[PDB]
Image 1: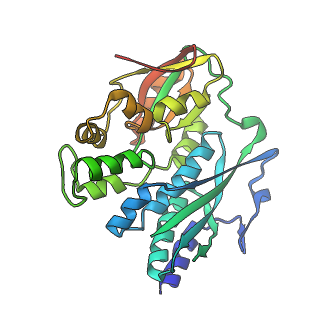
Image 2: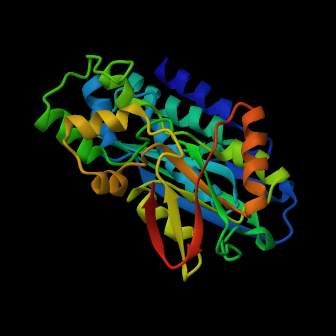
Length: 313
């Protein structure tokens, strides 16, 4: 049954270009000068929570999101994904649940799960491949002083800063994953397990109506480390504190862990999972457009001559 359920999950991700191992017929898409963008990633310490809660049908999404979000910031469209599950002994139902999350993420990203491997607690590793029109690569090179930074909200902690989280919730506060602590509105275990947002579909819609000069996926190192990766040399970012909603989970962690402001921004996404750089005149229109489709967005700052990220207000 587990195997049967596993095949059903994979089948949902299929797209017409997949030709029965699965091959991907790129020629069907009609790219003139195709450039392949790939990436690999592991969930990380967040996996430890999956173990403790015996809930494995969502971490697969985090895995897919980490690989896919990094691909789309370069302007690529995700094509296919492959997973690698390592474990002591393989329990069918367990593997089936891990794959289900991967498939769900793949469905959200629009990429097909064309391959997998279960080799004999566990560890998950994902690999995504995307493609972009060579002359349509988003490099951030055209970003100039004065451009606006529009941030799209994260769903929560996403997949970074879990080492610190585990230290705070287990070593320091000695909390229970089943308890509800204010300002959180659900059990801590559930909050810490919320899957990472996948921005693939949204960005594909946005890019059809607007010119995105650059993008940054907020992962390791937070806003501080990732925003500069999309900016040209000589250009820095000025973030306006209080221009976007800092999710409760972060206020919770700051309190329960007696954390300093700088450490926070150096580890957590603080509420923003993807930052977009656009010309000044595009900022408000973009935000309004997203608003009408039920997507919140915030003008979190602007770029300026210099380098690095600084905060104000």
